[PDB]
Amino acid sequence: QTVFTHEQLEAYQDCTFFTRKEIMRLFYRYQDLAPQLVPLDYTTCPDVKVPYELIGSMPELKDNPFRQRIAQVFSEDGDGHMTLDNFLDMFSVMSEMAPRDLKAYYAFKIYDFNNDDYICAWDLEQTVTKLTRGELSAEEVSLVCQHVLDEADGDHDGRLSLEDFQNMILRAPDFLSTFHI
Amino acid sequence: QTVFTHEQLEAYQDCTFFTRKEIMRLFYRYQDLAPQLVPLDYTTCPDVKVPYELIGSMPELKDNPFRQRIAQVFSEDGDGHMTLDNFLDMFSVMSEMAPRDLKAYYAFKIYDFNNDDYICAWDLEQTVTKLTRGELSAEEVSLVCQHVLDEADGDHDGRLSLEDFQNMILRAPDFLSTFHIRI
Ligand SMILES: [Ca+2]
Ligand SMILES: [Ca+2]
Ligand SMILES: [Ca+2]
Ligand SMILES: [Ca+2]
Ligand SMILES: [Ca+2]
Ligand SMILES: [Ca+2]
Ligand SMILES: [Ca+2]
Ligand SMILES: [Ca+2]
Ligand SMILES: [Ca+2]
Ligand SMILES: [Ca+2]
Ligand SMILES: [Ca+2]
View 1 (cartoon, each protein chain N blue to C red):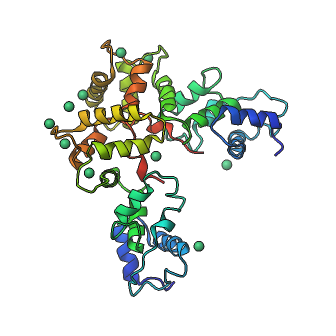
View 2 (cartoon, rainbow over the protein chains, first blue to last red):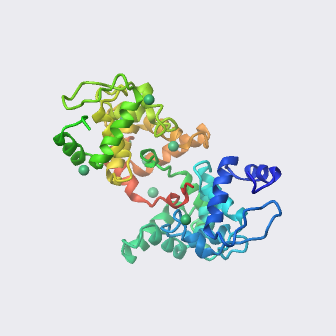
View 3 (tube, rainbow over the protein chains, first blue to last red):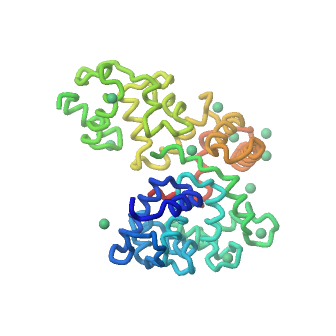
């Protein structure tokens, strides 16, 4: 391994859910996104960002309806252009090892399309339309979002706080997760 | 390849979601588990089971908290010891090609631990405890199970029918589905 110093690999393992072997694999994925831009020596702490377009188009994200928001939220400046640090943070949260309540924390940030710390009916409608791939009628999307609010809006102000949202997820385990390899 | 007749491979391609070639390669995986137990000629339909202990050690299952229940449900006799047909059926349902409505049916079967056709509060507790993998306290699991029942139990008999379970899954979006990305 000639990319990082021992210390900086220990730090990545300390601040993500990944093993050293996983950090190395993901580094090479990141470098391969923009091979004429990303250097192969990170021991000098280069300041490098891969443009959003080359992140969102990667195989693991290109079909995710929230790829732009995901990259924005994890990017250093909120514009989707990502350092290696940002990239590893993103995939650490997306990994199998991340607790569900932690995924729910970042999902809130991603679905809060206007970054006002609430998921309102408009944020919900955008989210549900995206999640459902545009196959529901705008009229039916709106009705689904009404249902979610009636269930989860604990203080009846018509919108979901972070706590509203995380507790909704907590009460809804992923019963179909068993039947996947 | 002298493992199967043309008609056997056609029947497997029909009933599973796999191609003939994928069936052959799944056979290699089954035979690999117990290579002096599983014969190479299946044209006579030999009666052979691979023990649960070998099934549950597969990578597809060894880290799945429900591996015992999965093997039990797909096994011919409910003990986790699997014929080739059981093995193919299991992988077919677990495959990406399997419709979500079919995965939901088998999820219900697996979570119905005592096979009495309902998910009661005890089944649900065992299920949610396994799905949350220690992330929740026992107290939190109980509170979640009571909520799940209260919201999904259509006829308020205190248990989930297959209809109740199906409607629950259909009722709301998986808000975290877009946050499971392996690399
Ligand atoms: Ca390439
Ligand atoms: Ca908002
Ligand atoms: Ca609220
Ligand atoms: Ca078929
Ligand atoms: Ca072997
Ligand atoms: Ca039962
Ligand atoms: Ca699990
Ligand atoms: Ca009730
Ligand atoms: Ca309700
Ligand atoms: Ca019921
Ligand atoms: Ca009652």
